[PDB]
Image (cartoon, helix red, strand yellow):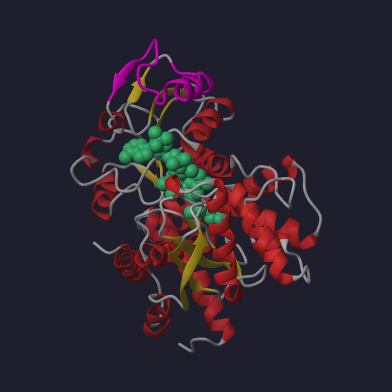
Amino acid sequence: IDPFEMAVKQLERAAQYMDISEEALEWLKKPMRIVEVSVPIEMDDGSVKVFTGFRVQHNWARGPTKGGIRWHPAETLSTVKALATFMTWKVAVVDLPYGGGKGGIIVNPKELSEREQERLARAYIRAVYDVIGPWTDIPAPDVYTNPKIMGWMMDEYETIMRRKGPAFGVITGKPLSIGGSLGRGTATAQGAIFTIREAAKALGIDLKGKKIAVQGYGNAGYYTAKLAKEQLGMTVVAVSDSRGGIYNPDGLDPDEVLKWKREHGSVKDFPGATNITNEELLELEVDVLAPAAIEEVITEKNADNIKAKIVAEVANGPVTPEADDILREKGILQIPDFLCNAGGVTVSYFEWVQNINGYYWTEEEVREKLDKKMTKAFWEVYNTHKDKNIHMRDAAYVVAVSRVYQAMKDRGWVKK
Ligand SMILES: NC(=O)C1=CN([C@@H]2O[C@H](COP(=O)(O)OP(=O)(O)OC[C@H]3O[C@@H](n4cnc5c(N)ncnc54)[C@H](OP(=O)(O)O)[C@@H]3O)[C@@H](O)[C@H]2O)C=CC1
Ligand SMILES: O=C(O)CCC(=O)C(=O)O
């Protein structure tokens, strides 16, 4: 249907478990500032093409808005608004002095050359300059965007700003050569691993020697499996991608699987393991399920088939609202998406702090700070879900919306 309407409905459903005034809820149901701009670039053939750009600042009560820029051909203002709304709750649930933001360009970057991509990034910066800044709106990498594009955008912003303030802090997820931070590459997977370890501690389950299945095998999924094996001592019994999946009960080494996928396009037909389809992976008998591929993979039609005791929602919205009740009834502990994959935005916040302070941290300090942040956030959410006897997603919503509501009331934006 409409992604923004779905996000608003999910917030409205969560609002019944907390004391929030009608005026504040109506304020939260609509983004505070939406910017639509034309993004013109000169193509290689000499012609000029105009693209549609988006930048949505949902709420900046707790601080400057934070959110990545997507470059998908199916990008829609509704999707950007929904993702900015989710970004607000994400930054609020880990206690960040941030707001919720999101940006996007309706473009197919596959048919764009490197020069054209750089021109697109620079033109997007030249178009959205007046509503962004290190203390206003901090973008980041997202779908079909990378640190290279981030560096181009940072350079354009610095050129326009005339180096008056810290231009490194305008955008996060850039290369280490220019204001980048360590631990950014594995940030999401590291945060997910921290939350999984905390969930296992909460359920009284030892993670050593337990099977894990990961759906999707890219920046999130591959690193999630690798860190689960290396840090949590888990056995990786199955991975998957867009093509198919592979299942080996005795375990799989993530590095070999990644090399095979890079050399053959997909993890399919990996030797020593059986080829299985994506839907069969979610129904395995594993200790932890990590669907880090796409949204809405666990529906009402397959929720009863899940046998994992922990479902780590590394991807954005992998479980539908209907499947949430079925999963909870079976007694499965669910880690909500904007809490499970908050490590990426937490490390982006660390990068922004380093940029604005002009002082950069080591990998160990970043890892320890992220560990503490994710542990505190997860324990807050779990304690809220146990105290009020509500769903984990509902508890995360209560925790985030309470913070945003308190910020709004302290700013005097709402009275009630
Ligand atoms: N920094 C991050 O990585 C962040 C991660 N997330 C969430 O993590 C998810 C993935 O992020 P990232 O790893 O960067 O993305 P990538 O696109 O780099 O990797 C996603 C993986 O999912 C696979 N995949 C694609 N379509 C399907 C499908 N229909 N069914 C099963 N698997 C599929 C892809 O296979 P193939 O490569 O063959 O296409 C790929 O291996 C997203 O949903 C995102 O919202 C959240 C916040 C930020
Ligand atoms: O780092 C950020 O600001 C956002 C990362 C991201 O893409 C997400 O959390 O969805």
Residue range of the region highlighted in magenta in the rendering: 251-276
- Whether residue 263 appears in magenta in the rendering, the answer is yes
Screen quadrant of the N terminus: bottom left
Q: Quadrant of residue 388?
A: bottom left
Give left or right: position of 181 versus 99: right
Ligand 1 in which quarter = top left
Please name whichever residue, 148 or 93, is drawn nearer the observer in this view of the structure: 148
Work out which residue is located at the far top of the displayed protein and give it: 272
Q: In x, y percent, where is residue 302?
A: 21, 40
- Pick the residue in front: 346 or 199: 346
Picture coordinates of residue 351, whole percent (x, y): 69, 54
Seen at 48% across and 25% down, the residue is: 262
Residue 291 visible somewhere in the drawing: no
> Above or below — where is 363 with respect to 96?
above
**Magenta region includes residue 262:** yes
| Nearest the eye: 314 or 415 | 314
Q: Whole-percent x and y of residue 120?
A: 53, 58
